[PDB]
Amino acid sequence: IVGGYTCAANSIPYQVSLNSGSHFCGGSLINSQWVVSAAHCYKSRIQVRLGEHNIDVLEGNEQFINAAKIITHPNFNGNTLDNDIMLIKLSSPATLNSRVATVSLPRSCAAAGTECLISGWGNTKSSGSSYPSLLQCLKAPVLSDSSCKSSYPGQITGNMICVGFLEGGKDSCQGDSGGPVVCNGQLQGIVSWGYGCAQKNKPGVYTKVCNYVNWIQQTIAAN
Ligand SMILES: N=C(N)c1ccc(CO)cc1
Ligand SMILES: [Ca+2]
Ligand SMILES: [Mg+2]
Image (cartoon, rainbow, N blue to C red; front, side, top):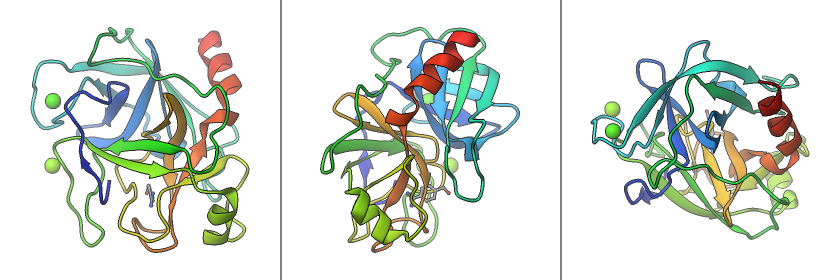
């Protein structure tokens, strides 16, 4: 997260860290046994770290649970990044408490201008590279489909939203991928792509979660 702030410890209780020896992507806990993330994050083996604030220290609220099943959207396209979404089934259910909690899936898509909360342990620098210990947060609005499409001509599908700023300086980044965009209590976005990070007229592009509730619920029910 570039241009953010340090979240209050455990204030984003649905945020997970996906770990394969080190943190590599975020995710969101959307059922006691399921995390949703980005398909471009795929690895064949994943440990899900719930309840984290400092990913570099064991502070006691953490639950470390291995992925039992990893399911990428069948129509994920690695070129266009359309359908950039993945589900992870935990090997045992997460235990839900104040520090580890599910986030609602969307009841509707979000209006342009809706304020959202973006979070992750990704890069915090717009030049160079710094990876934080502590979870980072960013408040940012849903942009119009128009403002999104003018920024990325021909590249925004109906399954993508832009969330962020046109001025630059405030965006998600590498290592935030897969993580949450939560707007009015609902998971509306998954960190997916953009051109660099926090550049002028290159807002973050996010998987449009409100188009995937049937895919998520159908995949959960089968497994
Ligand atoms: N600018 C962004 N929001 C952004 C986020 C994530 C990624 C993942 O490489 C690229 C860009
Ligand atoms: Ca920790
Ligand atoms: Mg580090």
